[PDB]
Image (cartoon, coloured by chain):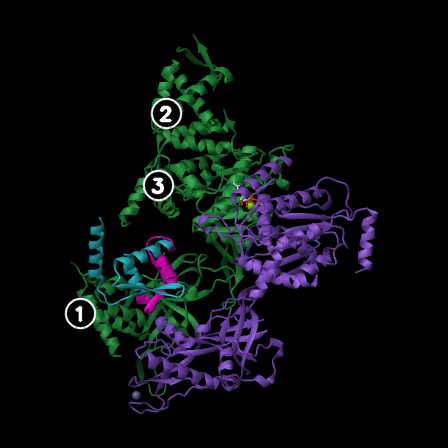
Amino acid sequence: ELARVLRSVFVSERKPALSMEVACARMVGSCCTIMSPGEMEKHLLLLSELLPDWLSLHRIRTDTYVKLDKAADLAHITARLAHQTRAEE
Amino acid sequence: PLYMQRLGEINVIGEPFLNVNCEHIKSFDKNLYRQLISYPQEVIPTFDMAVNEIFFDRYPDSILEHQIQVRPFNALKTKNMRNLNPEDIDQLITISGMVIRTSQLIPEMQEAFFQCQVCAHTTRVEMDRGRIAEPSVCGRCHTTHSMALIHNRSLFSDKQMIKLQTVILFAHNDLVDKVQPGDRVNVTGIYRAVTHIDVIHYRKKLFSEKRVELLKELSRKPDIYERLASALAPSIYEHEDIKKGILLQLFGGTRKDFSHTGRGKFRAEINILLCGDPGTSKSQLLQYVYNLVPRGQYTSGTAYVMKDPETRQLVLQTGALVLSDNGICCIDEFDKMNESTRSVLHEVMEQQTLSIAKAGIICQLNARTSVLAAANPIESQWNPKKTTIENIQLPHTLLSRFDLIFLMLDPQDEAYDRRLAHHLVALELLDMAVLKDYIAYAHSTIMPRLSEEASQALIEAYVDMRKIGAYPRQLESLIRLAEAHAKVRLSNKVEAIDVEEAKRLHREALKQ
Amino acid sequence: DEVAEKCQKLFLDFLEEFQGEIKYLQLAEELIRPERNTLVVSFVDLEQFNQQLSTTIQEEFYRVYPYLCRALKTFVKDRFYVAFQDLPTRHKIRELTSSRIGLLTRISGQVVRTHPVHPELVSGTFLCLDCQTVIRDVEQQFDTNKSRFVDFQKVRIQETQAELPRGSIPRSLEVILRAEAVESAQAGDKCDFTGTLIVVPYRLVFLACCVAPNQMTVKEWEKVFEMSQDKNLYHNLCTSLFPTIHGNDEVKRGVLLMLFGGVPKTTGEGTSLRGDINVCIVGDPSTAKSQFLKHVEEFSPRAVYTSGKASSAAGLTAAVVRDEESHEFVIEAGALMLADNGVCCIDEFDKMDVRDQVAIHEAMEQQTISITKAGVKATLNARTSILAAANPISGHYDRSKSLKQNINLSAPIMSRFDLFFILVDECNEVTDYAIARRIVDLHSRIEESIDRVYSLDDIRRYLLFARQFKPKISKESEDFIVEQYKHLRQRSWRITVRQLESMIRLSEAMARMHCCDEVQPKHVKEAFRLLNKSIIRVETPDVNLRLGFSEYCRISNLIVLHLRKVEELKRSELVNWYLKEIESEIDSEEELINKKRIIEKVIHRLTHYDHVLIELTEDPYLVVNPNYL
Ligand SMILES: Nc1ncnc2c1ncn2[C@@H]1O[C@H](COP(=O)(O)OP(=O)(O)OP(O)(O)=S)[C@@H](O)[C@H]1O
Ligand SMILES: [Mg+2]
Ligand SMILES: [Zn+2]
């Protein structure tokens, strides 16, 4: 679900890559659940480690920036995430 | 070449802005630097063209939001605001200043969108030199005077008017809203007269290695603290404990954020109260502190509402207390002040914040200041009594809020009068100038932290102190004093010596 | 615009193919109704159906909106205005810049002023006065019979308090509502508006279309369920809500109860009974008078904080100010009406003038504020819970004077607080040691010295879930309350019917805390103590292995009640009964042997020291001293 929101965020910002701070702040301000920024950061790290092809992270200077492929089909990605969750069970 | 790495970093991030240091241009080419100073408005387009061509040559597949713009900064002309002359018109200038007010977002047209009234033929006109080149004929039906301007379709740029402490600054596009009132900024921009300054760049370490080595050498002296006590206020005699307390207040404590705990930001800054007969060293000491300490404030015994003549909106002005944020505020004749102001003072003393709810205006302000107050006993003479209220008549709340209270009594001892008269008739330099930067370095660099031994010592001190009567606020003040002494020794850990010295000073003040 | 025609065709496609029933067919058929002329379309359905169209609409909303209206008209005519909802992104008022003009965004704010409904001429049929030529369908750039008019409303909105950066003046924004959006918003409400930022001659104005005010995830729901079944939920919540505060747990219980709050009731006579709780804390300095205010402010998002003297009468309830442009008089909101359905905290309540407290009087009890000033007549809701902090006269509780002489407050103000706690500071070595170690541990070990049973967000979710239940009062609770109030009232702070209503509210709050649909007498017994205690120490001293005074009284009460009930026993039998009754708490052998030790010691101590138990001749008979009540 959060991933979906993330997509919309990158749809809204007209930008190819965004910083951790701004993206996490916007996701928290738009998420259905009240969460801490650290939890959002760990969730983003988990998304990067599970699904690197869709979502990429780049270490620049003293920050890490987030880039995503907007042309990917959301349904197939959701199916892959469900399969991964089933496997982890 | 750092500029190729800068261009690569811009490529990675996609932000089309170049920051160029003017000293680098001066070193590389003095004539080019002179041309930049004389005619910035003509060399900036050339710089933009050159950097754009280089970047497109290196990486031609760049999808840039805007063309790369060059922002020179830190010109040699660091002229004072009062040194402006009619000679430097249309030249680059750099001014350091304080920001007072910032205007709202002002949209300015940069592309006029015109549409034919018959066939809906659309055209765009670039805005140039404050005049609109409105088309008179149609591009399809050739009908004269059939053009209509659409404000919504037109392109707008954000511009902001800012008052700098005064001069008027005009921030455009990206530079807009990057500066908050109450901050110190170095503004680099072109001077223009209609007078105003158009901003090009904003600017928001200070010690060489030899200075740090000298500071370490001085700190390795075990006597430096006492020597620094001798350094403070040379004209003041036999007030060594007062000088020690002033130095500890100058060092202050360390700031801690308790956001994870759910607690409010605890005060970490020291306040000292002085009480005695008038004509003593109170006023001179207050003047000395105000002059020595940067951002210091002197007041005698808050925010207010001002009507904006332009938008008829009620804006807020900051009093001396807010203006002295992160500084030291000193007050004379504390006793002679109105009770309403002293009632207000409780919040700033305790929570370091200030809340106003008046005439529908609700606001909260940060007030990180240290209060150094001087008071006069009500009898104008030290009547033999027991409690300080019996001589000064102050409420228990204000007295409990003070970290340190000192009393200036002129003793009836003849030798003291001899020494005072000799000091007067006979009425160091290496210390205070170094000490300003030393205090700045200590504030910026080091922060102490508490230990287990000091924990046990403080617990024992508290349980012993309560037998004399004791509030947890004096325990907090003792922690702050220990932190200040640890900063004095430039020690990253609070040890037994700091706690023992703080307890000694507190007990000496209580005994007196 | 070719892209506009493409957008119109794609919107027709979405209207005609979205689904196993097409959601919008019934809405389009109802659009024929004259009172219905705007269509509400979800943004999520638009984006899932196709992404290019969704992005184009989000980016060129002003460009394609008339084409969307044309598509709607064509679709309806085959068998009008378009409204959008559920945009996933929220934005701040300070974020509104010129770069966002024409973008479909939704903004959150609070309505402060309203203006009456006006007709706006959209397309006008003009008659030339020279040649009598009728010019029809003339759009307006910002014959009445043949022209088209649309209802209009103007709204003035202000920044929310939470989004307001410190030291910043909350900016105001103008909002234009048309057609069904008119009169859908009321002054003093917080709303999210979906629309665009248009350019008025320049000037910044927002055109809006819509207004804003079981399905929870499985794991959050299960966590809430599990924590709802905790037997020690009350104490765990009390400890977790104030992890860094030592002792004074009665204040913690009171503030938790006022956070839960009771239920409001309106009589058939139209009179509303307050379903909230007001709390007063008065104490000598150096206590935790303030810290509770800060904790409740940071925890509850609907909390407002204020100081005593700095607040005027106008700033608390409301003020009447003349509007510059309209040349009339309007109302500027006060703190109390901004704290609606929240909690308002006042610090240093004593320093406030009587002229301010008399203004507070009405909002205290009647829960509403009435203004009859300068030709302006109005009534406003003030549904707030007030938490007041104060110190006694001269800052120290002087025991040489009476209790009444130690509080400089008016009688009705004293009466209208449900809970009134007075804190007295005493010099005890064990309390000093505990306070010192807690403070130093917090100063040295900031994060590792915090053990929270439940997360703050979890507490917030549980409180939100619990506040919507409305428990019923049982007959047993009814007669228990009757007899308890009998006993209490048969004995300065006089106890009137207001205290009875407070007791009912407290029982309802206890019922809501435990997620019980009915009220039980145990809640009444719990609240009776809290209402009784009044003056309270920081911590009770230990009693000789040590045991607290409250537990000692509890054990004594239990044993006396059991013996007195059996009167209408043996030592071993009574101990066996006690261990049978306390089996719900013991979880280990060590706890059982500890409980046996404790009960043996307590029975011996009562037998030989307090004389409440008398021995009668290895298993001696025990009887109750006939003068214990
Ligand atoms: N039980 C306690 N646990 C932890 N800290 C405490 C406790 N009691 C007092 N303190 C400390 O003492 C301080 C005094 O609390 P405050 O509520 O700010 O003062 P106060 O009692 O309200 O007096 P006023 O009204 O500000 S003049 C707190 O901020 C804590 O640091
Ligand atoms: Mg307080
Ligand atoms: Zn034409």
Callout 3 amino acid: Lys
Disc 1 target residue: C78
Q: Are marks 2 and 1 on the same chain?
A: yes
What residue do we see at 50% from left, 25% from top?
C543
User: Badge 1: few (under 14), some or many (20 or more) residues near its Cα, within 10 Å?
Assistant: few
Contact check, label 3 and label 1, Cβ < 8 Å: no
Task: Give residue B395's quadrant in the image.
Answer: top right
Disc 3 target residue: C470
Distance between mark 2 and mark 1 Cα atoms: 82 Å
Number of the label disc, if any, that sits on residue B17: none
Callout 2 amino acid: Leu
Q: Nearer the viewer, mark 2 or mark 1?
A: 2
- Looking at the image, is mark 3 or mark 1 earlier in the sequence? 1
Callout 1 amino acid: Asp
Q: Chain of mark 1?
A: C
Q: Chain of mark 3?
A: C
The image quadrant in which ligand 3 is located: bottom left
User: Badge 2: few (under 14), some or many (20 or more) residues near its Cα, within 10 Å?
Assistant: some
Q: Which residues are magenta?
A: A10-37
- Tint applied to chain B in the drawing: purple
Observer-nearest residue: C297 or C473? C297
Observer-nearest residue: C334 or B208? B208
Disc 2 target residue: C592
Q: Is mark 2 within 8 Å of ligand 1?
A: no
Q: Is residue C2 left or right of residue B368?
A: left
